[PDB]
Image (cartoon, rainbow, N blue to C red):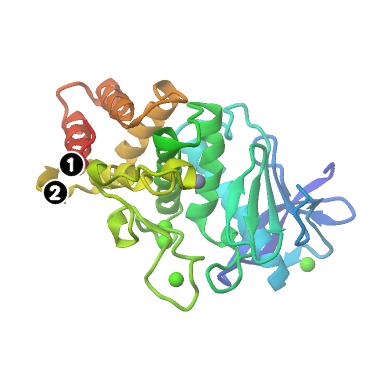
Amino acid sequence: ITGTSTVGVGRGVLGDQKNINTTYSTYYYLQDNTRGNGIFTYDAKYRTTLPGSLWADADNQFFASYDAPAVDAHYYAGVTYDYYKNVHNRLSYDGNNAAIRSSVHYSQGYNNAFWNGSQMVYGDGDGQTFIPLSGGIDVVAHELTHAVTDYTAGLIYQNESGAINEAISDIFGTLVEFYANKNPDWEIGEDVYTPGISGDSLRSMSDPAKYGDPDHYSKRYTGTQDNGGVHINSGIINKAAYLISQGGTHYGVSVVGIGRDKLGKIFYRALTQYLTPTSNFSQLRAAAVQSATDLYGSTSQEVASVKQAFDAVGVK
Ligand SMILES: [Ca+2]
Ligand SMILES: [Ca+2]
Ligand SMILES: [Ca+2]
Ligand SMILES: [Ca+2]
Ligand SMILES: [Zn+2]
């Protein structure tokens, strides 16, 4: 890890050419010394033991298919770091510039990715349902945002708190996708999901019910699956967030869109200054309204739009 900072070149999961920050001692390692205490990408070698080996390359050129997921994990972790620093003035996930670690090639045909409490972990997918998940930018940002949440609001992963947690992750994932301006959309996971099927995705913020998730509180999942539906009920918060930014009419309730940036500022403020581990949807509403009030003033259009948006999804 002690070495000379330099720049390598490679190809990502989708075949796009990419420059990446690397470190050289006797080998070129994926270690980025330009951001905080650094970004480290590891090879899990198809096994489940973590983190694995710090990625080492001989020529500082990663064009091998085996290389592709490491390139994107390393790179997109950088973009996400840049996002929080430049937009939100936050240094890494803990605010202290903690090192960011990612392991790729996790297990075999593993169709998920996650934050394990320490590092990010990415599967390669089975090549049918998924391709390597580090290929999506919103996925990377989604997982990385879990750390941010873990270090600030500490939303428990279960029931409504959990749903909020997931929603935050999707929201900021999407915002990062827009920030990097790489084929941005309000869909989640569209780049790495189901190769061979065009136009679909894992979740939709604009229209969750497309994939069977609730767009309204009365439609919320009350069962015990998925930790009480953290990946399901998130649709309700996701829809509200979409409406705040883009505006629209939902179940007869109209919302004036205030844009992405203000959405981001409002929700980041709610996340950092207000939400607690046990916060529910109502409390989230309160937090967001208070945040918007803090930033733009109580009589502002912004507050009004937050209100309208949460009214639309039936969260009072
Ligand atoms: Ca090489
Ligand atoms: Ca996209
Ligand atoms: Ca997306
Ligand atoms: Ca697809
Ligand atoms: Zn998540």
Mark 1 Cα shell of 10 Å, populated few (<14), some (14-19), many (≥20): many
Kindly tell me whether residue 244 is visible in this rendering: no
Q: Does the residue labelled 1 lie within 8 Å of ligand 3?
A: no
Instruction: Using the image as rendered, state which of residue 270 and residue 177 is in the foreground.
Output: 270
Q: What element carries label 2?
A: loop
Residue type marked 1: Ala
Query: In the rendered image of this protein, does residue 53 appear above or below residue 118?
Result: below
Q: Position of residue 206 (x, y in %)?
A: 28, 54
| Discs 1, 2 touching: Cβ within 8 Å | yes
Q: What residue type is labelled 2?
A: Tyr
The answer, for residue 97, to whether it is visible in the render is: yes
Give 154 or 26, whichever is nearer the viewer: 154
The residue wearing badge 2 is 251
Identify the element where label 1 is drawn.
helix
Looking at the picture, how far across and down is residue 309, in whole percent? 21, 39
Query: Which labelled disc corresponds to residue 30?
Result: none
Between marks 1 and 2, how big is the CA–CA gap? 7 Å
Quarter of the image where one finds residue 245? top left
Identify residue for label 1.
312
Check the picture and name the quadrant holding the N terminus: top right
Determine whether, in the image, residue 214 is placed left or right of residue 196. Answer: left
Number of labels in the image equals: 2
Tell which circle, 1 or 2, labels the residue nearer the N-terminal end: 2
Q: Residue placed farthest to the front in the image?
A: 223
Q: Which residue is drawn at 42% across and 47% down?
A: 170
Residue 268 drawn above or below residue 312: above
Query: Quick one: label 2, few (<14), some, or many (20+) residues within 10 Å?
Result: few
Residue placed at 53% from the left, 39% from the top?
146
Asked if residue 102 lies left or right of residue 257, the reply is: right
Q: Quadrant of the C terminus?
A: top left
